[PDB]
Amino acid sequence: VCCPFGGCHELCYCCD
Image (cartoon, rainbow, N blue to C red):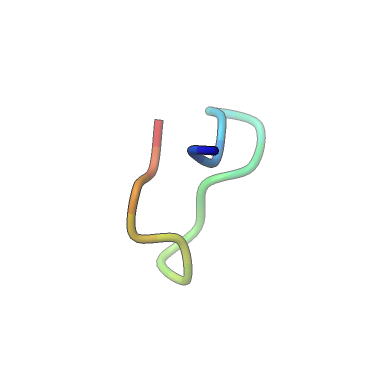
């Protein structure tokens, strides 16, 4: 799944 707003950092390609 994508990384939600309360989750996304540079690490996470998808990034909500």
